[PDB]
Amino acid sequence: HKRRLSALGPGGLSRERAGLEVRDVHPSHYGRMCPIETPEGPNIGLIGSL
DNA sequence: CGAACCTGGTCTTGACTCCATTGCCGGATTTGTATTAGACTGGCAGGGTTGCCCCGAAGCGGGCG
């Protein structure tokens, strides 16, 4: 629950404002953010981990 | 077969107690209203990034009495 990257919050995009393109894995994530671990609900890609 | 009983209540009567229920009556408190004389004179201030769809509004190029 620490080391968690969360792209939603005040100043950040909400889930209804969330497009499909922010939730993908850009190839700059390699070594900076894990492509595997993300919550499988309606938050897939908005919440990650370092 | 009758006498006398004592006991199931049935009901009343009177005397006494207690207790609510207004009734003043005065003080406490509670709520409303008014009044303060130097001068003072035009707001903060924030967010906001989806996408698609339907429709209505404003405008610009096109011709015309």
Image (cartoon, helix red, strand yellow):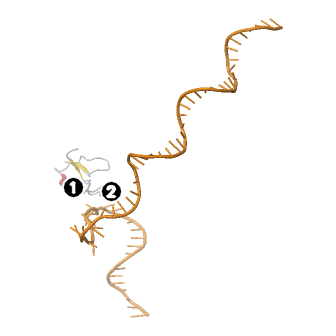
The relative height of residue B37 versus residue A45 in the rendered view (above or below) is: below
Horizontal side, residue B65 vs residue A9: left or right:
right
The residue that disc 1 covers is: A26
- The image quadrant where one finds the N terminus of chain A is top left
The residue that disc 2 covers is: A16
Horizontal and vertical percent for residue B23? 54, 45
Number of other residues with Cα within 10 Å of mark 1, as a class: few under 14, some 14 to 19, many 20 or more: few
Numbered disc 1: what chain? A
Residue sitting at x 19%, y 52%: A29
The CA span between labels 1 and 2 is 21 Å
The relative height of residue B21 versus residue A19 in the rendered view (above or below) is: above
Horizontal and vertical percent for residue B54? 42, 68
Foreground residue, B34 or A31?
A: B34
Amino acid at the residue labelled 1: His
Horizontal and vertical percent for residue B1? 83, 8
Residue sitting at x 25%, y 50%: A47
Indicate the secondary structure of the residue bearing disc 1: loop
Foreground residue, B59 or B25?
A: B25
Foreground residue, B40 or B38?
A: B38
Residue sitting at x 17%, y 51%: A32
Number of other residues with Cα within 10 Å of mark 2, as a class: few under 14, some 14 to 19, many 20 or more: few
